[PDB]
Amino acid sequence: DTRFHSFSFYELKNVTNNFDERPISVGGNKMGEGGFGVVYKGYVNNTTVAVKKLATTEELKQQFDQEIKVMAKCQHENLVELLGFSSDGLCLVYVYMPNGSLLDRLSCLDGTPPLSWHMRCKIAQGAANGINFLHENHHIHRDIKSANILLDEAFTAKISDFGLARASQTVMTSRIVGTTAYMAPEALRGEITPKSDIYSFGVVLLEIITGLPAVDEHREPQLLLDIKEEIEDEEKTIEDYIDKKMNDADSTSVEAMYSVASQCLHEKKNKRPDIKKVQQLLQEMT
Ligand SMILES: NCC1CCN(c2cc3ncccc3cc2NC(=O)c2cnn3cccnc23)CC1
Image (cartoon, rainbow, N blue to C red; front, side):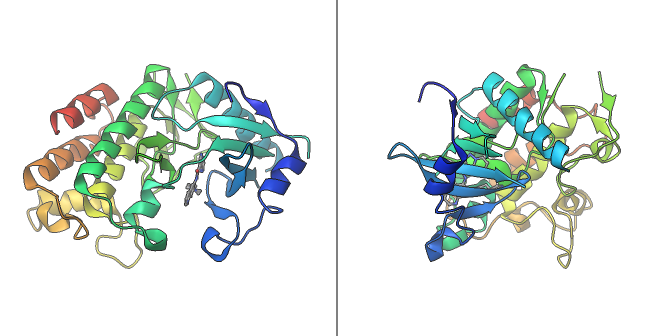
């Protein structure tokens, strides 16, 4: 509990009730899918944990070994903690995040009340501190989205899912990974740059302001990033997009965060601010 422990598959199989695919609310252990695995709630040393059971065969093992690597090298207060792993029976064990993810909380999943603007402000500051740490350590996340911004007991932002993280000039790849709805144009075209993480963070900001998912096949607009075009071509204001589930959302602060989101969502990757400027602008906001 000061070190990365190697877990027996039978210890994990046991504390997750044989990896009980049923959700928590019905009495099961499943917390949700993501990061090329299923996340189960476990119980080790009278202490709660989150167990990711991973599910090509060599591509997955690569993402397991990447996660252990990144998680040992990158330890910050705005990053999730790795407790241990298992390869004996592939499971990654993490410190449990009682408030799940920013995505679940923005959706008010399983009776949770909406997040206030004040907590939404601190979450965005925290997530930006987390990306800044990775970026300061020549790491590119590649899959920044609200589903993997996790929330602790004080609703502190804790960035997760490092399986696709790249450790480094803009380079190109043959294997394009990430979530379309959050991805910058160049990242969709095969480029690997921390600039693409900035763009992805910009989408996260609009999700925070509006409470809306990044993509909706029937909604107009379908892609949340397109609301920037509706605001620019004066058919709407950010005011019109503010999440109705808020009490405390002030217009001066909402417009300050949207100014940050707008800069992050620049289609020209070089015109975007770096994460240090995103941090300074978000701190100025409060
Ligand atoms: N996009 C994948 C999802 C997978 C499910 N996750 C969790 C949901 C929760 N629901 C209720 C209460 C506590 C919860 C904790 C979670 N997870 C964790 O505690 C957790 C800790 N590190 N970690 C890393 C990856 C995924 N989950 C976690 C949210 C993210």
